[PDB]
Length: 163
Length: 156
Ligand code: NA
Ligand code: NA
Ligand code: NA
Ligand code: NA
Ligand code: NA
Image (cartoon, rainbow over all chains, first blue to last red; front, side, top):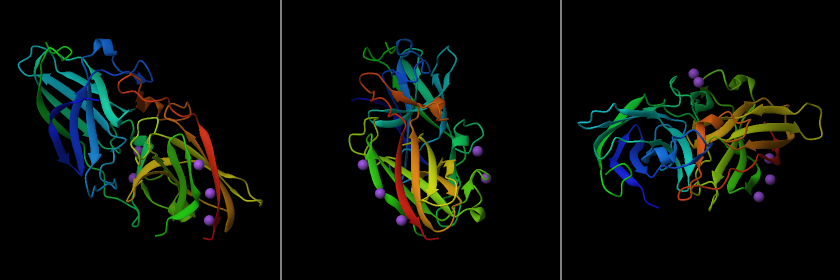
């Protein structure tokens, strides 16, 4: 299969944060993603643990229970920024955070993700996850909410809504 | 600290399901686990993907967003079954499903886990996790809720 990069990955708080996209997808439960026919891409946040991750994840593990908001802005565009809240889901290549998105035509875009840890009050998955704190099996505190940004160009006859 | 085994792992639906226990733990957020001072063990369900997992997980990945109920019963003895729901959490050896439990003294116990997929009506994480279904990136349907059982000898 093929996917497309948004910039290059960034390493922060013991994690690799990468932005990628592919064609719009379909998901179970149905009717939660924007319809694939009304979208240009499926945008994703690919988040995996680095070596010696402070929260106990082995290197390469997917980091679960995060909440990710995104803002996509067209450089020099007359449109309002594109925003949304990703959802965690599994595909044939494993779990991701993603969302189906409709863009504003070909051009340069700024992409900003805001990543919330699993103890943030803004993260609706926080009631479902814990962290050991005892001496023998405990880990370091969760990272604080942070953002990451990339620039990328979306353009071409082979790009849906990019020509 | 020792991680004690509860039987041997069992393989179903493209996953390894293993049971272990250790001493009671402390967790953030506080007030969800039974106090460590009022518990005997921390029981865990260790669930990881096997090769060719049908739901898209690479081999060895933790299987996330499941919901696990347990029933622990002192074998052929006085006492009611001990029941509860585990919680997903991370520790220094990675993520698990687990719970602090008070037992009924040394002896043999049956341990049964009932494992609910992300789309089960009993799984509270159903509004928060999806599965791709399109032809190019989709995976097979979720497994149906099932149980696995073992026994172990608690020494203290
Ligand atoms: Na909480
Ligand atoms: Na066994
Ligand atoms: Na088996
Ligand atoms: Na706490
Ligand atoms: Na045993």
